[PDB]
Length: 137
Length: 137
Ligand SMILES: [Zn+2]
Ligand SMILES: [Zn+2]
Image 1 (tube, chains in turn cyan, blue):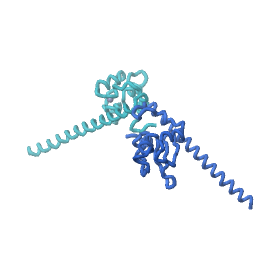
Image 2 (cartoon, chains in turn blue, purple):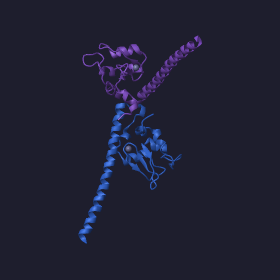
Image 3 (spheres, chains in turn orange, cyan):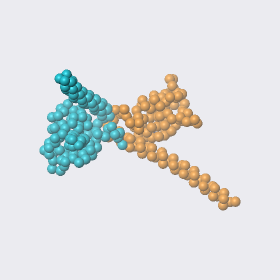
Image 4 (cartoon, chains in turn green, red):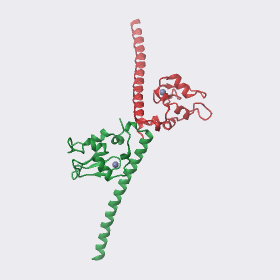
């Protein structure tokens, strides 16, 4: 049905992204529970339990079986409008839904900005060090 | 911003299809008016004022300046759900909107079916007349 860009708004889409997730039956942080919290699984060679809110884009690793994903999302990112959304998908008005997607688009830009900044700052330090060293010789 | 498949639900998208529409300021069937009624312009060399409901797919030609496009859509296609939609786009719930699109998908199939019927019937005549010409000898 829905365009790719929008699928992550659907719990079932999100749940389906957890394949090879280690915390199943018996655990607090099940794929159902991770997805109810907004998380999408997106693991790396390095961090294979990496999860991301689809809406605010915060990443969390180091999950333990007892972790309650809502309490964790709340702790890591209290700003996230998804956490205030009470209604189900189909109960939302298009006005509301379009508003939420505008905000997600902004959240995304923000993370891309803040990233480019940290990378730029780190480059600035390499360049600066290198010119200190040259002045020194 | 919205998938192509869905744009026609938007008045302004529909208005924008009227390219070379002859009934403008002064007329009852203005593009704004046609669009409010669900029509998209889709002319041919042959029928250059051809207009189609985006929702029930009824086609109407032979438009005159005093024609009110809602009264005409009502006359030509009394059972078109778009005509019951009182709410604006943004006021609809996704559940409602998904329901409406399911129905437009059915209306489309139905029209593709009824068209294929007419084509079959018109072929049936060519075959019939061709066989009569052969038997007569
Ligand atoms: Zn979030
Ligand atoms: Zn119609």
